[PDB]
Length: 287
Ligand code: NA
Image (cartoon, rainbow, N blue to C red; front, top):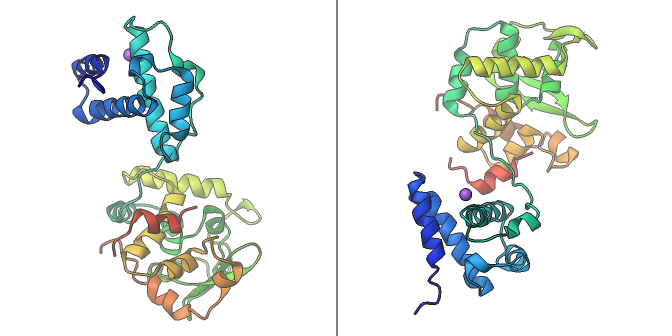
């Protein structure tokens, strides 16, 4: 009858609503405190350190995110108990925070890339953006690119794959196009660093262009859009990973050209003006 009735939890619930908190926030916190209490077999306001530690370690096979969230709800509960004068101690002081979960940044969207392609900019800025977003190049790969790395007749380029093993990538038509406006032999981005610009200024350029385009993210996020947008266009996971030179593949699987035609047909589907990507697929191209 009274089992599982936790009058003090309901007091906290009412208090939280009066702080203008939402039902979503409050009911999730209350459910967590009740879950811990029922599993431990204790009234939630009297739970002791070792019970809470046991529940956070053994009450479920929690993900890192779930454990982090649960720790925060328990911290809010016990801090409230102490602050309101209901309990002298706070057992969470004795419990180290769990592993901070990976913060999932905002993925760059097709509309973001549209605006990035539309910002007025020097052609070297446009080239850096195109290499990141439409070839998946990392900023140090962009910085060192030379005209003599590109075959515009065969529409290919050479870049480092895994380790020291060279890879041959098909060129997106947008990159072929800007390549004919760039040096056909020397560095695209001349600078003091082995003849080219520093990777830091390539990163800084892409970052400033994204701010100007109203886009949050970085050059890395454009390489992630490259993979994400390829998957959204129907390209199969393995081909995307080859086009990205993803390190889950071996240098041989990356540098092989048995799949040249699938790769070339895949990369050409990339169109920010345009097939269902899941949390599982996205983890396949993550880095
Ligand atoms: Na409080």
